[PDB]
Amino acid sequence: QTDGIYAAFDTLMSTAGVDSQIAALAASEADAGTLDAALTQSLQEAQGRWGLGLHHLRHEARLTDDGDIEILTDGRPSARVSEGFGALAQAYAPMQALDERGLSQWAALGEGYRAPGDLPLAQLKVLIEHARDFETDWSAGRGETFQRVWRKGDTLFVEVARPASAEAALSKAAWKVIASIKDRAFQRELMRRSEKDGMLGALLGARHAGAKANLAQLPEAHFTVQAFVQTLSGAAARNAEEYRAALKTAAAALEEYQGVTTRQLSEVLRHGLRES
Amino acid sequence: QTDGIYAAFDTLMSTAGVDSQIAALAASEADAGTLDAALTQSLQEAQGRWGLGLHHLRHEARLTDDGDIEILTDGRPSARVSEGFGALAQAYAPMQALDERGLSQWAALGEGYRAPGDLPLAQLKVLIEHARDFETDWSAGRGETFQRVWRKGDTLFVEVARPASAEAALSKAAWKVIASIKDRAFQRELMRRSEKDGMLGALLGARHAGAKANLAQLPEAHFTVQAFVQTLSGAAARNAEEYRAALKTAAAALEEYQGVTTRQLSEVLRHGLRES
Image (spheres, chains in turn brown, yellow):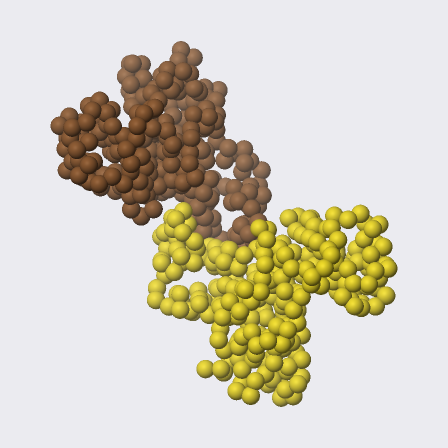
């Protein structure tokens, strides 16, 4: 009932393109402090990619005596992996504050002044070079993306985000997955239930028993890639050239990981087609 | 440049499920008054099914000396078939007044009082049985449909409508049509351009030259089935039992013709797949 938990964590992490390899690390008999550090590292990466908007909280995950993995924010028990992925998404929901574009409204640094996102590159240079902590608001970035930047202590953070809901991603991963099926009326009656209802709807109505009870386990229904944070440290975190390069890097990686998680999703969705 | 015009009219009419057979009627050497009557009859039927909301206008179509077909409303030249189907949709646009649900705001009878759509069936019975002209506002009808009823002179009209845009219909007819293709990256990159843009978009970007110049000819991009008017005449038009049956009939036919036009669309869309 709490077994297959390392693998459950690994699958959650995969929806963010994080090959956390936690199961393998436990099979190698790694010490529990090691597993704890690895769980936390992966979760913080995933948090960099999920786009939920919670950089102002501390994200940890840790083993419990009863074989569970406990996820926490600012140290408060938020959820347990055994309670399922929908339960985790529900745990995060009240701590979010998304605007109309889906972008987070919270300041990464917390309460305080936020410089504009459109700032002239010379002004931003002065902030990078000579300020202590600082933070810009969202600005448009390229190809329907948005970007921002902030420095906490010794580390500069460059975030690039293109919000995209998880439901839609699932339905398009089911577009490819159905697309690979017999040209037949299962299709035409999914597609004619596309001019009437969402695609989990038409695919839970046109399928057989356990389509919903099976799919209610997928983490990809609650989590998907929407941003990418590239970090810099030390002298680089006060160098404007490094920041410009890091922005290029974060946009590139956004493209990459969106593609990669799409591929892994359609693959395992197609693994469910062979099983059927 | 104005040849293939009877067939152009026939194809327009097909988007509403009207097998007008105008081309065949001309090939039989029917007199031009006959062709004129048939063009008008078909167009008025199509107008009953397209859902544009223009029952308060008189719809005629007539042959011109130069081999064209002229479409008119209240006798004003509105458009010519040779100008294309997008031109006709543009001709109709300023005469519409759609609400948020897509349903027409114009009263079928024109300026005047409109009884509520939820009226108690006994009150509606008294209107059917003893009023002269009368008209109800839209009301919900069943399965996401809407319905209304009005009497002009000797004829009672029962309209049942489930608005559904033409763009969406085209994209779902292209879902089935692609669905029938090689499980390959043409798909995965249409479906990953589904989390970014409309489907005419992803299918005009992933295809080759003339996808847009060819598709810009389809009438189904501007017209689709959205309603069905069932009529009654004579004594039946003042009989409440006949009205209740006619409502059942109009909803059934709505289902039918939505299905049938979907089938004809995917068929000719799939005929374009074999041609490619």
